[PDB]
Length: 61
Length: 73
Image (cartoon, rainbow over all chains, first blue to last red; front, side, top):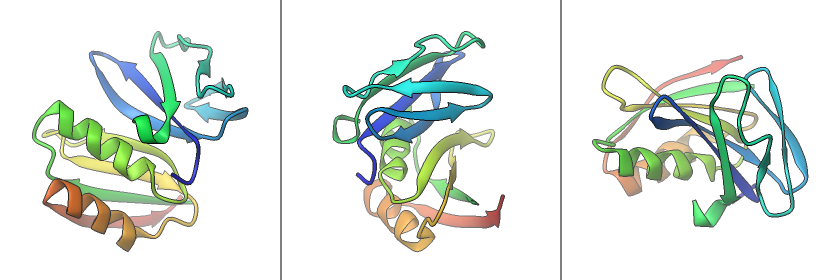
């Protein structure tokens, strides 16, 4: 757990991509900017490619 | 900015999810991806990743972990 959060990305029936982030960090996922709040929740939830973002603290997976 | 590719024994979706989370836990990892026609390769991308420690962790928890490639990017 070097970063607080894991953002999971669900597209086409599976999570095949996950990204790390600290709370209140903005990361990039493909071309898109994602903001991750103090509860590890990502904004926006639905990326423009209709993929679905989900997050939580690292230990909860 | 290194890209690291790892064969991991992850035969079902629950182990693909465990491996994804496990690689992500390692210092310097920004992203982890599942690739290969048999859903058995992790592409780990970050900065300053210790790839020996990465593969050892996946090996300890998934049984098999082979370091296929490290590459600048």
